[PDB]
Length: 50
Length: 50
Image (cartoon, rainbow over all chains, first blue to last red; front, side, top):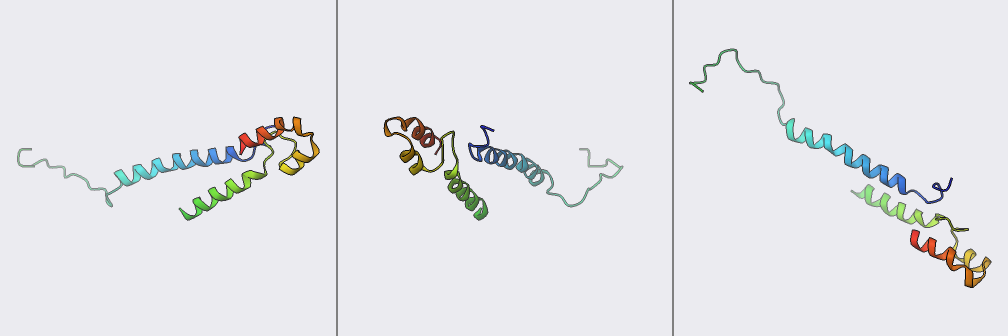
């Protein structure tokens, strides 16, 4: 009851935390998901000696 | 960006109607209803909150 008269500081804090937490998935997607198809290596390993 | 700036400005404007533990949000009511040498203890908390 005493906290609800202080305004909406906690709404701003929750919004900031949500904005911080939502961008980690965006960072991971933009770093690792640059490929469109899942390529598979051939069973043979004749790479010229490498 | 436009929406977040607008909502931040709107939140800042709407924060002016909070009580912050004072008798009322209206400054005129505080300075008129209460006796002047004892209204400072009500003015200061509102000032600090704003």
